[PDB]
Structures are given as C-alpha cells and as structure tokens.
Amino acid sequence: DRKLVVGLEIGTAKVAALVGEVLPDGMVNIIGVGSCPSRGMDKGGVNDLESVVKCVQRAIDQAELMADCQISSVYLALSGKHISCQNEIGMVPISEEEVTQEDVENVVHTAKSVRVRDEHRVLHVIPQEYAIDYQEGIKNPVGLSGVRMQAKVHLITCHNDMAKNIVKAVERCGLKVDQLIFAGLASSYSVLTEDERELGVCVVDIGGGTMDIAVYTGGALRHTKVIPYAGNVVTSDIAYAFGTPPSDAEAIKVRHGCALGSIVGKDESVEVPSVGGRPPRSLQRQTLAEVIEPRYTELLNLVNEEILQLQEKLRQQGVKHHLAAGIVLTGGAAQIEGLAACAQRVFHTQVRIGAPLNITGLTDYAQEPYYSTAVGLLHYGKE
Ligand SMILES: Nc1ncnc2c1ncn2[C@@H]1O[C@H](COP(=O)(O)OP(=O)(O)OP(=O)(O)O)[C@@H](O)[C@H]1O
Ligand SMILES: [Mg+2]
Ligand code: NI
Ligand code: NI
Ligand code: NI
Image (cartoon, rainbow, N blue to C red; front, top):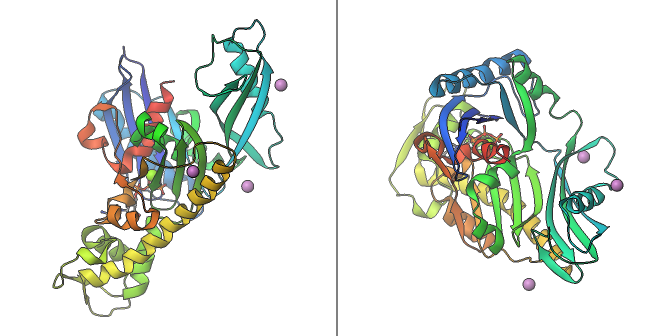
C-alpha cells in the first residue's frame, strides 16, 4: 500500500525532490514537493560539492516534511552534453515453437552486446520492436508461435564520469542512488500519452541549461538527444542586448518575456536597471520580444533539423517516420508566452505545452512543466 518512490533532479536553476506514492491503478500520488534554487553548479557540472549538498538537502528536507516520511533512496535524473544513443538489432531462436520470457531477455541482451565506444557507458536498454517470421511491429511477443525472432533496441549511453559528482552529493546526504535516468526519458514518461506515442511524437524539455529530446514513432522510442542551449542563453541575450545585469535580464524575461513579437501591445514598457552604475533603461515589451523570439527559433531549429535527420533515416528503413501527434514542449523555459505559436512556425506541425500526467494528490504543486522530468522519475521507478 505504501512503498514510496522519490525523484531527484539537480537542475541548473532548481533542485526538485518529489515523494510519490504509487496507487493500484498505476497513478502516482504526489505527497511531498521539495525545491531549492540551484547553487554551486556552472555551465559544466559541479564546481562546489558542499554547495550543491546544501541545496540538495534543502529540497529533501522540504519534501521529507511535506509527506511526513523519511527519504532513503532516490531516482537521479541525468543529463548533459555527452549523452548519446544507438540503434541495434538482435536475433535468437524461438525454441519450443512458443516464445518464452527468457527468449525476450536473450534477444535483448543479444542486440545490446555490440561494441560501445571507448569511455562510453550504456545507461538505458530500451527495446522498441520485435519481429517473428515476417511479422513486425510486435511489442508483447511472449506466448506467440514462430521459429526465428529479431529484436530492435535503443541504447542510451553516457560517460563513465559525467555523473560521479552529483551521485556524491546525493550520497553525502545519506541517500542511495537507485538508478540514473536520462532526463529526456523521464520527461517523456510524464507528458506523453500512449496515443501520442503510437501516432508519432517528439517531446522537448527546455530547462535552464540543456534541451532533452525524445522522439517516439510506432509506440517506440526512436531517438534521444541533449542540446546544451536552453533558458540561460535567452537570458544572456537580453543582458547583452540592453546592457543589463544577468539577474535582471532573467527577471524581465519571466515577467514580461514573449517568444512572439506579433502579440505584444505597442505601448507596454518595462524599466531595466543597467550595468556599471548607469541609469535604468526603459525599453518596450514588443522590442524585448523581438530579442527573445529569434533565439527561440534558432534553438528549436536545432531540434527540428535533428527530427528531419531522423525521419529520413527511419523512412529509408521502412519504419514509421511521420510525427502526426506533433511536438510537446515541456520544462521550465517552455512557459513563455506565445511559445506554442512560435514553435508552430518552425516544425510546421501542431505544438502543445505539456504538463505531467497520471498523477493525483499535489497536482497543484507538481503538475507544472518544470516538474515533468522529476515526476517522470516516479513513473519510471515503479517498474
Ligand atoms: N515564464 C517564463 N518565461 C520564460 N522562461 C521561463 C519562465 N519561467 C521559467 N523560465 C526559465 O526556465 C528555466 C528553468 O527551468 P527548469 O525549472 O525546467 O530548469 P532545470 O530543471 O533547473 O534545468 P535543466 O533541465 O536544464 O537541468 C530558466 O532558464 C528560466 O529562465
Ligand atoms: Mg529540467
Ligand atoms: Ni562521447
Ligand atoms: Ni550473449
Ligand atoms: Ni513518408
């Protein structure tokens, strides 16, 4: 009745710790929500271990109190520039004419047994499709009849050391790390429906530093990618354009920003403190949107031409390649006004801002786009 699951993300602008309770119908009951503005981490990783330990424990302490429980283990969200993916294929004999569960384990281990690059470590082994004698597109093949079976898997890889620092901070707080999970995978478990997965969809988590991408076609995970340019780059463009402190460029962006310059009133204006003991700067909301907008299109175009690069790859191998469900933009930096209409002009398909699904309890606090990554760590963990 009461085996909890805890998800922890040490983001670049936030440290989210959520305690969830899994219910009989698969829905996760959110009973604790902890948060802390991130500290001690720069554009690379950890630059002060004791600094992030303070902020990690602060979020854990907040979640521990809200749920009246004692956290002992977590599912740590992992991201970063050096995440990569591989698509492999295996093959194994359907002995006994009937598919055993051991056969699926054997054929998945066969496909993943390829030669992974030096200094690279396999993080996730996700089967995507099975084939039993000319019949493809199979997801649950156990119990069926056949002679030869082929399996296709998605291999998410990382580096041997790119998570060593954040694992210490969690352990320094007296916590076990149950599993490292790619943020894009966890984000896809929160905002994506199985209807959207079959129809073909791509989920993009726009955080403060990274852009975690996952593309699903035919109900199968086909692509994962991190792009290390997110909300902080938009801020630095505002601080650069108007000569402002980066802390007040982040403030004017959250309160007055807009990724679409066509929907801003002409005479709305916001004051801006300048750098170097110089006076305020009274720009206009539409002019400010004229700086935010082209940064968002350039970022989403980096994602668009990787989808296009993926579709042509999938289209040639006879695999479902069209994204009919569209794009789901989640994450904290996805809450800017006019982003959906702005992202529509880049992908030329339907776009929607996604929030975590299949949760109860404290949805008021957790059903936010900047919680999709850490809520998905709960959805993954209960399996
Ligand atoms: N209303 C808003 N408009 C524009 N940007 C916003 C808004 N609210 C938040 N952001 C941006 O969201 C970013 C942080 O989002 P989020 O909470 O998802 O980050 P994170 O999980 O710490 O980071 P990452 O996923 O990159 O590790 C910041 O860069 C901030 O500027
Ligand atoms: Mg995030
Ligand atoms: Ni590499
Ligand atoms: Ni083997
Ligand atoms: Ni086609």
